[PDB]
Length: 115
Ligand SMILES: O=C(O)c1cccc(O)n1
Image (cartoon, rainbow, N blue to C red):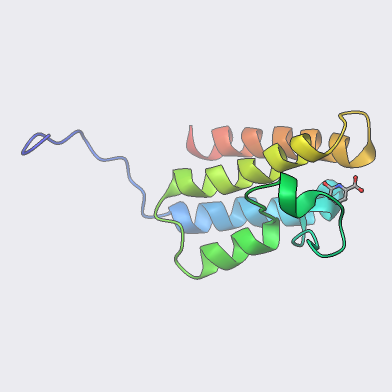
């Protein structure tokens, strides 16, 4: 609170560390469903069902242009990709399995890098 500050975690390297984690997800072989925005004019249901679409290229653009205030807002957009994937796909499908795999892959890198 006012004039009572908790000790400050060092955040100076967060931009480059997030950028690196994103690079690794972009090159994972199961990233293909998540590389580009879903086409809302061509894909049934998506625009109406998925209220906040997110994809790796949109995250890369936001990261490169100063649109993430901090670590946590970046992790929220990455998790959003995989939450959208669960909402729109059966677990028992190739895309549904790709989402589960990419999420596991992300959270491990997250813990290792920061926790
Ligand atoms: O064909 C599908 O099941 C599909 C298409 C677009 C996005 C998405 O999540 N799934």
